[PDB]
Image (cartoon, rainbow over all chains, first blue to last red; front, side, top):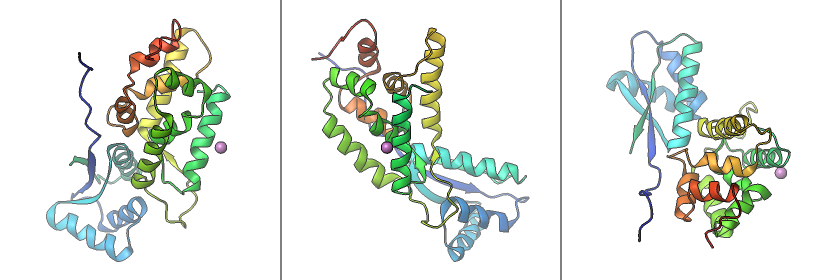
Length: 91
Length: 146
Ligand SMILES: [Pt+2]
């Protein structure tokens, strides 16, 4: 006998903020605080991470939560008219 | 997306999220809530699912993985996940296209399966329940696994 396709629990995902030249530094610090509950002197250090490396992991959530967060961040960036890009990363 | 019975479940799901100050209203809170929704509970009992085990599994998972608000913040009480919005739209679209005008907990239960990548869909499969099983119970008769 058998039992349909596989299972495997959903994977956790990394939420990432990509760097760009048009988004002002202050706005990214703002996003890190508003959507990641980051300490002022932690978000600020994390913005430096994004600028320096060109990309930085802002957190790790379930696939479900990560997807919602990415969408909240990008919608916000868009409404403020900044090309701030937030992305999803498996593992 | 209304059924009184279903609306109650949705109310309980949100009240629970807000109680633990959860930042998000998950498909897992939804299924957790549906466990006491007669329509849903019924289809799951017909599928010989251990509700006690499922309930424990769901509660453990949402406490360990759901982000908690800063206790301060504005109030912005619980943001439904995109997955959550999708299962509801799916259940609503199915009912509307069937010519009926009532969305039951069981319809919602069915829509959850299409959310691959949700812990909820994973836990249902783990308990040997498939979309087809719920669909067979909903229609025809009590086509039960038992
Ligand atoms: Pt309640």
